[PDB]
Image (cartoon, rainbow over all chains, first blue to last red):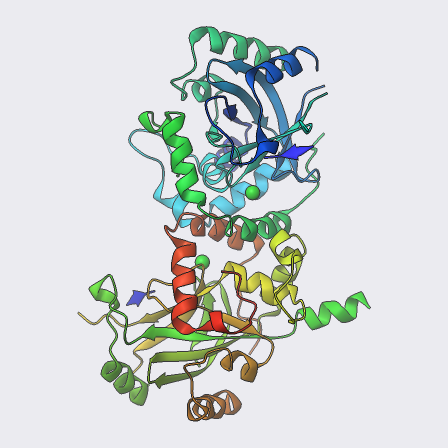
Amino acid sequence: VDNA
Amino acid sequence: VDNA
Amino acid sequence: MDEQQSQAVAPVYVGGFLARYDQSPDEAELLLPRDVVEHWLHAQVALPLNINHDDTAVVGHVAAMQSVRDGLFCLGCVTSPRFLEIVRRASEKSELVSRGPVSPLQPDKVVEFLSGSYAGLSLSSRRCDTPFKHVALCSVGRRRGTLAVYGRDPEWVTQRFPDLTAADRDGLRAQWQRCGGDPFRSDSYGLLGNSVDALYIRERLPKLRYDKQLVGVTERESYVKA
Amino acid sequence: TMDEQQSQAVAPVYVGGFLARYDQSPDEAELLLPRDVVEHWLHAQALPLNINHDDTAVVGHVAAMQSVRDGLFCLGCVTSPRFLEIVRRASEKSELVSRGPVSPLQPDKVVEFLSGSYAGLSLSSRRCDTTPFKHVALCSVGRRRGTLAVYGRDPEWVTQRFPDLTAADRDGLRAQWQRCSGDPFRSDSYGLLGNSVDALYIRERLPKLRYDKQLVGVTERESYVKA
Ligand SMILES: [Cl-]
Ligand SMILES: [Cl-]
């Protein structure tokens, strides 16, 4: 998962 | 008075 | 007046783009093209809304997500009473909040504190090397154009973005009308702790202004502090 | 022991740094504070230590003030248990604090949180348009440049962070903080949280902090400074  |  | 205090702690809506298709991320991991977004949207119950990706700091949910000409836009709703009460209290001690909003907007301490502290939106999705996990309110997002716009009325917030079309809004209105216990598990100390982190994000203001200009919330009047 | 570590974290914390630098031309006339004036005022006229000039947020006192070759330098002491407890709790929730300090410094959550949140010093004195000096405030950034705040558990160690100071300089300070009522803090976490959003909108905060760091040479030393 990528968190911005 | 002056506050910095 | 416990009357004013109840009005301050009422729900607060937030909207803004989670990603802008015409913006090349400074990091590959942040790429999120229209095709992927639209595919993922078709596939993937409401996504939780939290503070800076902390799952113990959930303050509400996402009421609507919509892919439009310029990017992925979303509308969320801060409903946590505990979180709102903390914000209420802090807003009372912010000089920025005391100066109030611009032109003809009525002051709204809670909304203003949220506008200043969490001026950005940050999506949490599956890596590209249920696709959408959650949306986070933060000091600044890593993807540009992710300015967060707070307001008491969902229509009003959506109306802050000049890029959106009437059709665009109908698609959103349909969603937040369909969707229409306190999930927050943190406290003031937690938010205070998170605040010092925000103070060391480089070029925070410049990025915020850039986002403001890109999404045109500059050419509108809102509670945005950047 | 948690209660043991927690007591160590809530122990007093010293802070030092310049309140003003003589070789810096303020961007506002109201901020002018030359050596002659400072030294005169010092000869005439313990000052409270507070958060961003809020008199309901007093966290300690100034233990020493000294005019030196480069400016007016001061050393204060954060003693408020209520304030320290709040900081302790918040520090536990800061990713910045979790990453810890540099090179060989031992982690110190409370000290680190203070270093990050209140990286600057701001003097409160009579206008220049007896008691000339009112108080010193810990803030996100001072309006006068070179006012970087340096936190540490030992007063000697903190004073040793500034390469400009001389042994004589330190003796003058040591004399003061060695010669020198109840928790004076009257605010709370919500207050500090409210103050935090204000800090987020001070323009060029980091650039100014780095500039201060370089000017005072705390860059060429190792400390808990986060800027
Ligand atoms: Cl944040
Ligand atoms: Cl401050």
